[PDB]
Amino acid sequence: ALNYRVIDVDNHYYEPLDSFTRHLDKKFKRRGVQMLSDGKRTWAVIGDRVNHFIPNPTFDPIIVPGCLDLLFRGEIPDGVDPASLMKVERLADHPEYQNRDARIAVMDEQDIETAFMLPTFGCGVEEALKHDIEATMASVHAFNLWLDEDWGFDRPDHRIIAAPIVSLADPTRAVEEVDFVLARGAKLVLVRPAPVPGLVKPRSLGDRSHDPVWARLAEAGVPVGFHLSDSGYLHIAAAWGGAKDPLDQVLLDDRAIHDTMASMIVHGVFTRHPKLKAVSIENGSYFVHRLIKRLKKAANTQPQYFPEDPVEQLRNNVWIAPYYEDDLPELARVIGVDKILFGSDWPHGEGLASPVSFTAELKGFSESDIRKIMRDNALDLLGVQVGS
Amino acid sequence: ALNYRVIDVDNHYYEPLDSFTRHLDKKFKRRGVQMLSDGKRTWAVIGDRVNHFIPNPTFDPIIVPGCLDLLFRGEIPDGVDPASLMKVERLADHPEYQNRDARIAVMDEQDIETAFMLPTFGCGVEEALKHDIEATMASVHAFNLWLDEDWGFDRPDHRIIAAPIVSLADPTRAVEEVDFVLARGAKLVLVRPAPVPGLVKPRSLGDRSHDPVWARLAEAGVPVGFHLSDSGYLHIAAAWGGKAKDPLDQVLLDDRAIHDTMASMIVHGVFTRHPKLKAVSIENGSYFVHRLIKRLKKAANTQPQYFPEDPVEQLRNNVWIAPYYEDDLPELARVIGVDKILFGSDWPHGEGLASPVSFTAELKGFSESDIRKIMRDNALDLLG
Ligand SMILES: [Cl-]
Ligand SMILES: [Cl-]
Ligand SMILES: [Cl-]
Ligand SMILES: [Cl-]
Ligand SMILES: [Mg+2]
């Protein structure tokens, strides 16, 4: 057991059915999220289209944390049926998934001082609304109001950093959203790792029209977080002719986070906003080495576009929560041990059952480097030092 | 200098303006390729849309072989300006780019025994025709006729293996194109590393309707080659608001097409059903291999039911790779086996080696006999 509490940068709640409706402008009652029932099952119907990002939006019954961990690692014994790995429980047996007081008490048992609390259902909504910019902005605001109500962006006990969503789909309205969440004390905001929807056409994350948003975050010392989402990448499997076809995930994997970080870096977001901090959550860290190779090639062939070294921008401005099976010594060699974050993804089935068991993956590190990975790097990410 | 002649699996001709029209029936005169001119420049106009795969389809002036080496490796020296690199000569001064006799004499000077001769313009046509299945199949047939005429799939001197194109867009017609080229002695065919266009929707390379084509190639011992092409991957840049080049575009494209092509072949069981089928990757690099292996292993662990064989072993057994000059070649041999590494110069392209045999400069970490595998013998195994 560690001698200090940890800071877990990847935790989830399970949204109640009204997370996107409780505070939604009635103008968007059909344009946004609706929960409709066939009598047995509830379906999320988003802009009049049934959405399938979450198989059961009631979240009951609910997967056992970590039951898919050995699977996602490949550690699964021979002849064993993967369907047999999934175990579920009654949602009411786990109030800590939806209730802040219950969650804090579980955090105490888990030895977590501060958890970043991130959406589950909410990570699929923006792709569903990508053709309705006004419904996107209203729905993100409704969600953020719900989030601050049930979880709180950062209540005075400083146990939970609940990250609201910022959509850049309407960049003027986005500056209003950022001002609103910053005024309510947000310490981390999530932007989807995907092309930004547009009225006319989609935009790069580094579009100059987004500069006012990045400037607000950078001046506030609040990082942008990029968490695994529906980023619309099934379009690749679609181009290839695409109950799970095994090809789809091979074609998808970690391409969204790679392309997101490329968009940010190549289009000069960190050049224009050198104080801006970013963090990748639940996207793995395998993307880094290909991204570094490709950035080096781009900077060499078009040096005029790279007044600064894009690899150093990656190393300076970006923190990464790796997957448990990633080569962590190698990652530290590449991005620096100070940029590696512990995140458990609790209570998801693909996450760790016991968050602090992440330390089993750190036997290659000194006691003081483990303290950085398990606690202090996250505090560095959130903070801005007076000396910087 | 080596004491054997080499086998170069990546060489090009430059198509004359009529490669896709000489033997094309008039019914496809507008649906296929036309060369239309504005008084100064000539443009490839494909299915009534101006195409931009090749900057100048007359190929005159013509790039100096190897002058873009530094650029394609991102080894442009400190201080050197990128656009100062391109040098051009006149096409008339290099008949070996379009004339078989002149090319043989140049191969003698280069110490190449056999060259795989591959398209330049031809690698962009299929994407342009992906919405017209009949025009695709007819245009590929017309081109294959032109190829056998000017270069010959495999003339008696056995100096040149000129690979015809096979499109799977109409699978029945594809089987018939395979028979056509095989009967004329083809020893390698090119399939585009890209989704296969369909009347109704695109298909995986491993779609079951493609089995008769793979079966015929596997039984004949003729490999399928996948050469760098317009595979339509600019759609990813497009999704990001893309499409002076925007430097993001190429970061988002890179080697994704060959990765996804090999994934489609292996995951959908082409090598499971056709274990004798040989494939070769040409001008796509070899960096894709490590991520592909990672992802194939994950897929096999997650859905073992779909993977009765080890997909990484299928990669290693059935696939040959001509890597980029600058790739880590000892590492590649550690991963796929030295027997699967092929020398290819990409001559005379600008991004290729000016001197094909200089490829050996990157092989100092290998034994004399392994260099012989890479520069000659592995290609003989691939062909059979
Ligand atoms: Cl700044
Ligand atoms: Cl492409
Ligand atoms: Cl077979
Ligand atoms: Cl290279
Ligand atoms: Mg082997």
Image: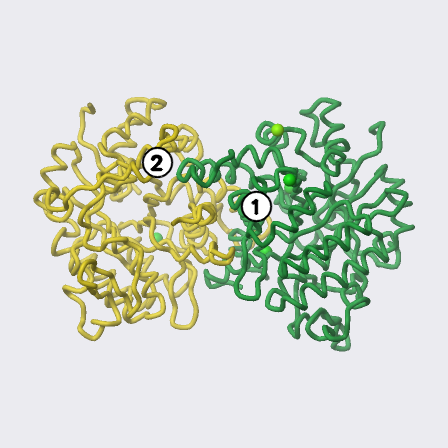
Chain colours: A yellow, B green
Q: What's the residue type where badge 2 is placed?
A: Asp
Query: Please, which chain is the residue tagged with disc 1 on?
Result: B
Secondary structure, mark 1, is helix
Q: Quadrant of residue B202?
A: bottom right
Give how far across and how far down residue A270 sits, in percent: 40, 51
Q: In whole angstroms, how far apart are the C-alphas of marks 2 and 1? A: 25 Å
Q: Nearer the viewer, residue B308 or A295?
A: B308
The mark found on residue B265 in the picture is 1
Q: Is residue A221 above or below residue B126?
A: above
Q: Residue at x 47, y 58 (%)?
A: A238
> On the same chain: label 2 and label 1?
no
The mark found on residue A81 in the picture is 2
Res B149 visible: yes
Q: Residues within 10 Å of mark 2 (few under 14, many from 20)?
A: some
Q: Is residue A12 left or right of residue B351?
A: left
Q: What's the residue type where badge 1 is placed?
A: Met
Q: Residue at x 74, y 48 (%)?
A: B67
Q: Nearer the viewer, residue B142 or B252?
A: B142
Q: Nearer the viewer, residue B150 or B95?
A: B150
Query: Please, which chain is the residue tagged with disc 2 on?
Result: A
Give how far across and how far down residue B210 sits, in percent: 60, 52
Q: Residue at x 77, y 55 (%)?
A: B180
Give how far across and how far down residue B225 sits, in percent: 68, 46
Q: Quadrant of residue B62?
A: bottom right
Q: Nearer the viewer, mark 2 or mark 1?
A: 2
Q: Quadrant of the C terminus of chain B?
A: top right
- Count of numbered tags: 2
Q: Is residue B206 left or right of residue A252?
A: right
Q: Is residue A120 above or below residue B301?
A: below
Secondary structure, mark 2, is loop
Res B323 visible: no
- Badges 2 and 1: C-beta atoms under 8 Å apart? no
